Image (cartoon, coloured by chain):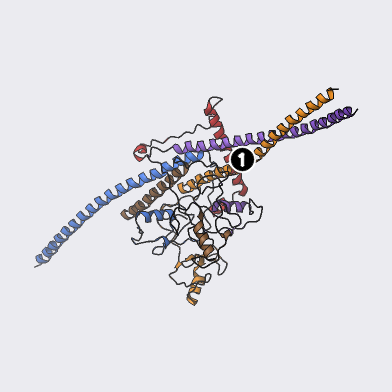
Chain colours: A red, B purple, C orange, D brown, E blue
Amino acid sequence: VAAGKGEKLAAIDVQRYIQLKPPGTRESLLQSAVVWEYQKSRNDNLYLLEKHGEKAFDSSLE
Amino acid sequence: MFCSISGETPKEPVISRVSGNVYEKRLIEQVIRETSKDPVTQQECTLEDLVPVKVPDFVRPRPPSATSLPALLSLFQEEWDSVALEQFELRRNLTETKQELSTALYSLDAALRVISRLTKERDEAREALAK
Amino acid sequence: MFCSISGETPKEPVISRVSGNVYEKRLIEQVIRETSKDPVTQQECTLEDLVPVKVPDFVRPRPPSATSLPALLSLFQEEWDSVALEQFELRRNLTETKQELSTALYSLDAALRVISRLTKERDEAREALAKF
Amino acid sequence: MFCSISGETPKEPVISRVSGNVYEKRLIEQVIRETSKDPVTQQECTLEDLVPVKVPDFVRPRPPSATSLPALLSLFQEEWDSVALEQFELRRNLTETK
Amino acid sequence: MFCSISGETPKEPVISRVSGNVYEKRLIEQVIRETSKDPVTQQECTLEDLVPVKVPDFVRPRPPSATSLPALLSLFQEEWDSVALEQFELRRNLTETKQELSTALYSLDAALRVISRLTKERDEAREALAKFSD
């Protein structure tokens, strides 16, 4: 990977999970299902973050 | 070694004095942190109810060939797809079991109605036979 | 950050080798001078067993957040065990629902056979009524 | 993967609470029947001390497939650990050469 | 707050006896696996040399957007690239510092030769002055 990215050559990975492909083949179903699961996990994580607030941030600054 | 929790081979099997069953120490400790009660017997459980045990470890598959190795995302996508399919099938099981429950309710209701029919018709037939 | 001997924070924290504890220099040297024992674990201790802080060092630190690869990999496995725990609970619910589904299944099949037999009896009774 | 009494692969993993060692259910039962004491520390042992019958139920065991997440997770961690070790060694060499 | 090896924040820091420095378990374990010694002191070390001490642990506050999702894979690639680029910078720094050290050492040796030669010329010049005085 070093001989590769010695000329920057930023490695690429799929970020096309926000395009929200319209009704099509099974790929549309897969994207919708994975986006739903990502959304549920995001809900859980952010509500968990706001359960305690920024006390952890205050401790980090201290 | 057949772990009753997922089916995967447990690398740290444990035993229980009240009812020995295969779990992992970290998961049962975390559950007791959530709810300090025995899930099966509905009785209070403490942190000292488990005895230490030794384990012999296992092997790993260690994928070779080191080519930009982005397959992690595809495996992740497969994992969420599997859990989404299982959630859909949870929904299907709930719907089907409720439909069966309702169908059973009306089946037994119809049995009552048709047995009222039977008793009345048999009484009529036997009385007219007596006549 | 708390010293068990006095209850106050140590200005210059020191870690005892014999037993892991955070003391302050003055009191720990007092208890070392008075006797060669640990005030907490009542075990032999000396001046060398006390470990001052060697924090400075020479290497470059990181932010204490989820932006480093050990930390980021910890969050990776946290996401993985979160979806794993979700799968655990939902598979318990699946097997419980399968058990009650099977119970309802044989109950409904028996009920359907009962309905058929009963309706046969009632057709017989209707014929008996119509015989007159 | 072997017993401490006979040496065969134990199909039924059993362990005494009083003493931590690998044994076999039949041999430990024979020892208890012959002498009602632990052979190691001379402690009492009862039937409920032993591991009961294994309970595989509602498991649907997927075979332990090779291609899986833990291998990649561990590989990434070992990689980062080695590369960070390299950073340490060469930062020490850098400060020395400076 | 920072493990002395990589700078990482040790959630389970340890301190040694021959040289007490904050270290992380996994990295010293892999060093022992590679060489059963401590390169810091060039001395034999065992697994027991570390003592598990008590720390309040470093709280890890999450960024505005870190909630699983492809944010996590983008961060995977970004930190890959970042630590690798750090490695490149540090390797090229090795090469530049060693070549500069060699050049400096050659200049220093030449300086030693010329200071010796010039000192000898001083001795003959001083003696020439003193012997003119007669």
Instruction: Give the image quarter of residue C52.
Output: bottom left
Quadrant in the picture for the C terminus of chain B: top right
The percent coordinates of residue C105 (x first, y second) are: 67, 36
Residue C6: image quadrant is bottom right
- For mark 1, give the secondary structure: helix
Residue at which label 1 appears: C94
Q: Is residue D6 above or below residue A43?
A: below
Left or right of B64? Residue B16 is: right
Give residue D23's position: percent from left, percent from top. Answer: 48, 58
Q: Residue most toward the left?
A: E134
In depth, the one of D59 and E67 nearer the eye is D59
Residue located at (81% from left, 24% from top): C127
Q: Which residue is most to the right?
A: B131
- For the residue marked with disc 1, what is the amino acid? Leu
* Percent of width and height locating residue B19: 60, 54
Note whether residue A45 is visible.
Answer: no
